[PDB]
Image (cartoon, rainbow, N blue to C red):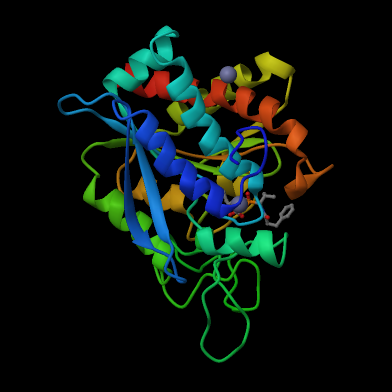
Length: 304
Ligand SMILES: CC(C)[C@H](NC(=O)CCc1ccccc1)P(=O)(O)C[C@@H](CCCCCN)C(=O)O
Ligand SMILES: [Zn+2]
Ligand SMILES: [Zn+2]
């Protein structure tokens, strides 16, 4: 039984992708962009009313298995799109004019493992040469200063960069999807938790993107917007100096592909519950995050 106000296991979320697609055929279509290490389908939802030459925003959740509020958020975004389409002017305009690719869970194998065996697992569940230690950090696995700072070379470490950039089936599938759809994807959003932040490039070195001032202003206004609802305080800025250096990130990789609006979100909280954010915070967290995401979406729409 799926609920947007609880954490849903992978079987539930997978059935939800199919059902939400069936119930909303004018607004949603579903594809699989690849399969995981363990062979699970990586589903992707395309949310938007059909039309010609539509720009797109790409958003993924569930890079990191233990970050359950991330997975819940991508589901909430879809909830909002279908519920409010037609009644709320902004969401209606967004869906009419842009497509949203929502990838509800990238690291499906890790997610299953947090439900069955280890709530605090972060990495993929693939094997490594020369050791019994499992998995790669998918957010150290992209070809963006790959494996150079803030990433480990030890397969037993939580930030292990992998055997090569895109060595993981899941990160290969996401990078392939983005490469194949580069001319339409105008923004890349990647949802994580916790620590309450809106980050933009760069994390792989202490350097700033060409459109630094624009991304800084946008991130500042989006955090201001998020706080309107419950007063939740976010920080923002370039990854390396705002959270820590961390090479091989998907936001930096996406940005270096030419996608000018590339953000990583770090949802609630600031450490009281950390990864184990209680289900009773799902609603408030997703609602205030919707305000930031809609703010970014509206800006992208207005600055094509
Ligand atoms: C708690 C958050 C910050 C997660 N970080 C961790 O789980 C690493 C371990 C940790 C660090 C800080 C507090 C608690 C745990 P995260 O969401 O996974 C942070 C992201 C930040 C990457 C750099 C910015 C975007 N390129 C990551 O480490 O991949
Ligand atoms: Zn994360
Ligand atoms: Zn709402």
